[PDB]
Image (cartoon, rainbow, N blue to C red; front, side, top):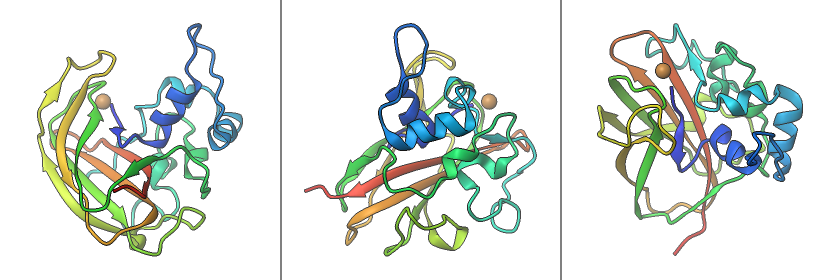
Length: 196
Ligand SMILES: [Cu+2]
């Protein structure tokens, strides 16, 4: 159980945006409000649970185009709204060419690979996210953890050298492929290359 925390995934950033001291969910970001209204609060309480029990490392030909951010709509929860092709989702501001510290939730820890992909130049978030819009840029095998599994703020951590020559909006998609299970996790992070 986990999705990306830095650059944060849609469900993670939306749950941070909605978080209140009583546990009520009150987002101010409009894409987050829309996703709450469509798919429900359960998605944000379970922001880490974007999973397909049977994916088994499969991607194109199995996870339909336009459904990556909800694990093909095969999870135990409704994450369908987190596929909305909108440009107003919360996003992380990045510098093209910089190496950044990546954090991925270890809400429940598992052995495996993190397959990290970046949308191609020219792709923008008002378009459908398909496999042919993504390029595999890194695979991270069994990275280390900071914080115990199931504790607030706990995460896997590794470095990512961001490609040069990029600008404007993009998305980083990660597939967490367990080595001990067919269960995989699906993570989508809105970013913009406007730094430096
Ligand atoms: Cu898990």
